Image 1 (cartoon, rainbow, N blue to C red):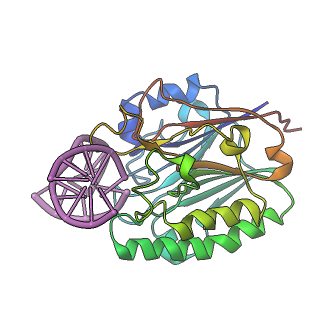
Image 2: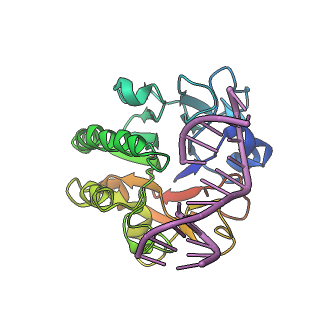
Length: 259
DNA sequence: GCTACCATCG
DNA sequence: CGATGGGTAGC
């Protein structure tokens, strides 16, 4: 009975003072993938490293209060990979992998390119360097879940006003069909869309105007699953009862057995 | 303060 | 449509 959550905490300390720590236990989650810690190893308290006795593994950026992802788990990972293996994106801490035998879960914070053009390009090199990486993992022959902020909305149904954002970062054509290739060419399963092909399921809302209140949001938080495991998904939900961030926790369940 | 991260008006 | 301005966490 497996349960995985993907939450972009927008600063783990802020989220913790907004009630995320209690949520980690309350949700009953077995594995929690968090992105955008906005903190370093020294900035982390004991509770932000091993919440409720869970094991934890993180990858922080060089500069302070920026990016950083982590993976918490009720069980001890028999393996852990920090960073992807490339200097350019590993100096930003955007990747953590945890192997639990046959299972393999990953917290990922794909770079955003909405700040500037150069950021957009770094995002593209990230796509071009992470693409073959996705392929390798598929050919490993194991159950793998890739949770995180991909900062890309796949189709028109994945965001409220898809008309005004066709020229903006996160919903550019080449991005959209980069994701399209990730789903079809490699056979990765966009779990939410597969479980519910007609439900928007927004996971992020801008700080602008009445974005959150009017439900003008994006679905940029994913759990890309392998087929043999994707077929074991039983349900999914976007938690919005409490607000720990501008993002919302993505909860997915799997009829699974670790034995 | 500064830096990084598209909804709303005309 | 295109032009115009943002709240938030952390340094």
